[PDB]
Structures are given as C-alpha cells and as structure tokens.
Image (cartoon, each protein chain N blue to C red):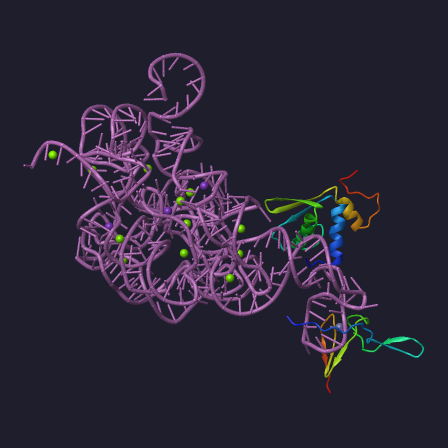
Length: 91
Length: 58
RNA sequence: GGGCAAGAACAGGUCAGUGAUGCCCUUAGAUGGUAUGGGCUGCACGCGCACUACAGUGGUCACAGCAGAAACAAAUAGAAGUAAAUGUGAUCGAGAGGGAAUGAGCACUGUAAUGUGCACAGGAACGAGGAAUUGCUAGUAAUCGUUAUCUCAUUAAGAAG
RNA sequence: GCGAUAAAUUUAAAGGAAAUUGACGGAAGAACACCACAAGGAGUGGAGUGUGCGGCUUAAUUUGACUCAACGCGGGACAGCUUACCAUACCCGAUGGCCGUGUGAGCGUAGUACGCGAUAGGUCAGAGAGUGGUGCAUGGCCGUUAACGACGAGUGGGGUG
Ligand SMILES: [K+]
Ligand SMILES: [K+]
Ligand SMILES: [K+]
Ligand SMILES: [Mg+2]
Ligand SMILES: [Mg+2]
Ligand SMILES: [Mg+2]
Ligand SMILES: [Mg+2]
Ligand SMILES: [Mg+2]
Ligand SMILES: [Mg+2]
Ligand SMILES: [Mg+2]
Ligand SMILES: [Mg+2]
Ligand SMILES: [Mg+2]
Ligand SMILES: [Mg+2]
Ligand SMILES: [Mg+2]
Ligand SMILES: [Mg+2]
Ligand SMILES: [Zn+2]
C-alpha cells in the first residue's frame, strides 16, 4: 500500500483515539488531521474493512469508516495500549 | 526488470586493530552523516542518500 | 398564460449519469491510472435544421430619443458591455445591393493558438427560387434588438427568458 | 353428357357449427382539431455560410439514436481536461493458507556495492476495479398513445358459458 511504519502507527492511534474516520475519494490531497495522502489512508483502512474490523459507508464523495466493538480489542493489542484504555466514544 | 545480486553478511565496511578497536574501512560522507560510507570503482567514489559520484583526476 | 395531472400499454430510449444492478469478458506486456503529443474539426458526394441576402417601402453621414429597469478601473486610429428598429435633415441613383475564398500585418485569453478582436486590400454566387413542404386567430403572426440566464480561461449564427 | 360408384396414397384437425371480446373496412350516422381544412399571412425547398447525419478516407477520424416520437439531439459551443479513439513513455496488486525471510523479504542507484529496511516476495484460493459487452436479464427516470374521456370496486339483474 506504500506507507511508512510511522504513517501506519499514526492511523492506528487516530482510529483508536476517536472511534471513526472520514476520507474523500479520488483525491491526491492530504487528510486534514493526519498529513497523509488521501488515497493511502483509504487503502490502509480498506484492509481493516476486509478483516471485518471496520464498517464502511459511502455517501456522495465521502467514505465514512466506523470501528466495530469487536475490533477495539484487536487494535488495542496491535497498538499495545493498557487494558484500561478506551476510545473517546466509550465511557 | 533485472535481478538483484546479494553479498550475504555485511562485515567488509570495517577493520579491527590488534587491541580490538574497530574503524570503518571505506571512507565516510561529509554531508549524509559519518554513518554513511562511500563506495569505490575506478575514477568513481560514490554515495547513498544523495547518489552523488565524485570523479577522480587520475 | 403556465403548473400538476387516470388505468392500461410499449420486448419505445438510456448498463456512456449513478458505491443502482444480474451475467459474460479483461486484469502488470491491463480493456486500470498518469504524462507528453495527434484525432474527435479529414473531403468526391446525397440529406436535415438555422443565419445573411437578392435593394429604393433601399445604402451612406450626422443628430436626437425610448425598454424590460437600476452594478460599468482607466483608454488620443482600433483593438467585450446600459438597446435596436425608430424620429428630422442631408446625401447616393438602378449590381455605391451583397460580403464568400484570400494577402502582409496589429493586439487579447491561455501551460500551450489552432480560438477571438481590429485595420487595410480583395471583391464569388445570388436579380425572389422546380416537384414538394412547415407553423400561425390578437398584443398572436412577422419585424427589431437585449441577456448581472445557461454553457463560459477564451469562444453563441444554440437553447431558455 | 347423365345415372350409378372404388382403391393406393396422405394428414391432427377441417376458411366444420353458432355465439363473445377486439382489430380492420375504397360501410352508415354523430362529434372534434390551424401538429385538419376554408379565408388569409410569413417562410422552407434554389445561392453563400454556420451546425448535425450518411458515404468515403485515415494511425485514429471513439460512440448512441432512424415515420410522426433519429439528424443546433446525448444539457455533444472537443486547443489541454472533457474523452471513450491512436503513437510513445511511466506507475500499481483486500484477505487467507502454504512456503521463504532481520544471518535481510523486497526497494533506490550514474546497478555491484553502496543507501533503505518488512512496506511492497513467490504459489493456490479469493476479492476488488473497468466511458469493456448485453436496455431482448433488470431498477429508476423519461418520451409516446394523450392530454384523450375514459377507468376499475361493492351490491343487485340476465345468459350453459
Ligand atoms: K427559399
Ligand atoms: K434535436
Ligand atoms: K426502462
Ligand atoms: Mg427496443
Ligand atoms: Mg462529432
Ligand atoms: Mg455596401
Ligand atoms: Mg448544444
Ligand atoms: Mg354423376
Ligand atoms: Mg388552406
Ligand atoms: Mg437552401
Ligand atoms: Mg402525436
Ligand atoms: Mg491526452
Ligand atoms: Mg478515463
Ligand atoms: Mg463504471
Ligand atoms: Mg425497451
Ligand atoms: Zn552523501
């Protein structure tokens, strides 16, 4: 997918910090909150959707990504956070 | 595209004194950090992070 | 004066509007993207729809003057913009009507002229149209301009007002 | 010419009978309408140009649509983009199994010894993508019948239907 290891962990932490992501299709521009190329962010999240970790809904020109509960844990193992840590959407 | 030859375990970059102290055998780049070493072939000395080739006057 | 507008139909049109879609096909030497160019605008020829005409109920010069309403740096020949038919006086006198093909120029838009504007030359057919054929009953037809409407970097002889 | 009267062969029904609903009539009777006419008015068809269509040419001149209801139509006024077509060049690949890998998978290079490192290796399954095909596999939306007077439900009546 052609992302650096730094860029990969930047997406992992964002997607855990906030339980959602929003990406614009057919764009060579940079994602406002990450400073990563839009097509590359789409391609990264694509894998998480295929793995069944993330829902995808496509509306007009935007892809809305939602992290499932049964995948918060997988991303918590992957990102090696403490067992007490949860997203802003989870009390 | 072409095939990539491989040189196994890279240890040739260094030399070891009788005291066990180690020093680089190839010379080192001034502008890419001293941790980047410089190749040799004929009139050419060359570098990695910059692809710059020096041409010797010999 | 518009707008909304039965039931039933049609193997009527669109997979080239669609993260609407079944099935077949291709898929790193791609039928996927991108970039630089060329074409879509080629020319013996037959057709459909529009635009200027064939003059005197005209052409040319100047002067006025009126819309739907309200937006307009500057510019010394000239190089987008707030009507035009029209009203008065002059002029021209029966191809001084008409502006097609073309020359060396002078500018503008643009990443790039091949596109557009301007000045000078040049001056083709056409002298009211065979067989046929299309709308239109009143502020209608026909005439005359105009779009802070749509296309639009620049381009209307197109639509929609 | 008449009277009287066979076979071989062929075939699933027969312009067989009466009635019913439609479609049609160079049948009758009512209505209606300048996409009909009468009474009129302006044109189109002829000329030059703008634009679309066929034919032929080309490396490519990408393509749909054909009586009304194809042909300034696809919001189709194409220098790039649009753009599907032609010439050259460059770039890429969900996941899962197996195997192989930091003693270095693969990548960059003035390509061989230097720089970067799991990211992007091979093979089987399986995804996804495509202005690629089929509107005679569809949905949606349009146009046309038609802007026409018709249109079905419940209860009663008649007929074997
Ligand atoms: K005519
Ligand atoms: K049309
Ligand atoms: K349909
Ligand atoms: Mg059909
Ligand atoms: Mg064309
Ligand atoms: Mg004249
Ligand atoms: Mg048009
Ligand atoms: Mg007899
Ligand atoms: Mg008549
Ligand atoms: Mg004509
Ligand atoms: Mg009709
Ligand atoms: Mg191109
Ligand atoms: Mg394309
Ligand atoms: Mg498609
Ligand atoms: Mg059909
Ligand atoms: Zn260097």
